[PDB]
Amino acid sequence: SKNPESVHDFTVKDAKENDVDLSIFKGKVLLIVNVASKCGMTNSNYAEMNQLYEKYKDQGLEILAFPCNQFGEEEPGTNDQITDFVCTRFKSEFPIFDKIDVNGENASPLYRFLKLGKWGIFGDDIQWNFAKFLVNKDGQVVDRYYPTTSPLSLERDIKQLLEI
Amino acid sequence: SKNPESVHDFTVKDAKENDVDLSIFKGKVLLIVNVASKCGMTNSNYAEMNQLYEKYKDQGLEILAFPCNQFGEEEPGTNDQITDFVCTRFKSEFPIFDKIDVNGENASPLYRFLKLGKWGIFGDDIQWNFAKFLVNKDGQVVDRYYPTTSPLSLERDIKQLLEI
Ligand SMILES: [Ca+2]
Ligand SMILES: [Ca+2]
Ligand SMILES: [Ca+2]
Ligand SMILES: [Ca+2]
Ligand SMILES: [Ca+2]
Image (tube, rainbow over all chains, first blue to last red; front, side, top):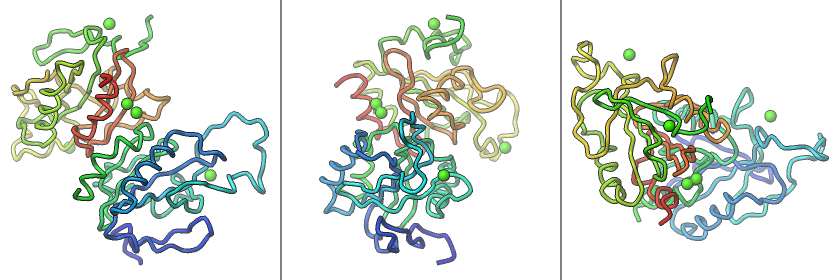
């Protein structure tokens, strides 16, 4: 809409560049997390996220992954590609949206909003790849975790947040 | 080893101003929490850490709680009162240390070091009362949590560090 009140007032692009009204997720627990551009998903975060999905997929937990190139201070070897460098694919169970920036000038309105969560307690810049956010059924930012917190460690909060 | 390599390379004052070398904690997993400076163990965090402690003190978990008045020092109807500006008494099984600054020009050297953790991923200033850090048996910072993350939600990582 126009009054950033909830995460549901936001619409984002999916991998297909098609609009997705986040408002369709109400009633479900949103676990928002920024993923890397790397092409391979080697990181352990994905595996653990899959499990989390495997377990709470049909219970209200929806994982919203967002590719971001603002980190991964890669050690180049043939990366110089400005016409097709971002991974042209993301093989995972949960949904992977269009690549967006989480920090800086062109930051996504959503992350801007996720950052106002809990009176600015969540106001920090996304520290690195895989920062985790938990949103309740009403679209309010409930929790935030550092990249270094494996998805599996968010189970207790996921569980509670679902009333299971 | 002039320049600190670990949390063990720091000496802090305890509630009774007696120097404490963090080396006496080597071989133990540490939960470092900054607490409100005012009196009152009513905040939910206390009960949860209390529980955490009762269930892990005798397994390798130590809790270093540091009082700080940098957050909402304007809370008590009568806070203005300068006779110290930190509660003269903090009933708790787990040790409460002397007051320290966590942010700014007088931030405790220990908090400067913890903010160095994970290649700067933990560089953010302490957001509010009750931010959490998990340090391994070796004295290196391995996790950081937002104030909003309840203690009990750190159990998985604790067990993982204590190896259980
Ligand atoms: Ca960019
Ligand atoms: Ca971890
Ligand atoms: Ca020492
Ligand atoms: Ca003030
Ligand atoms: Ca851990």
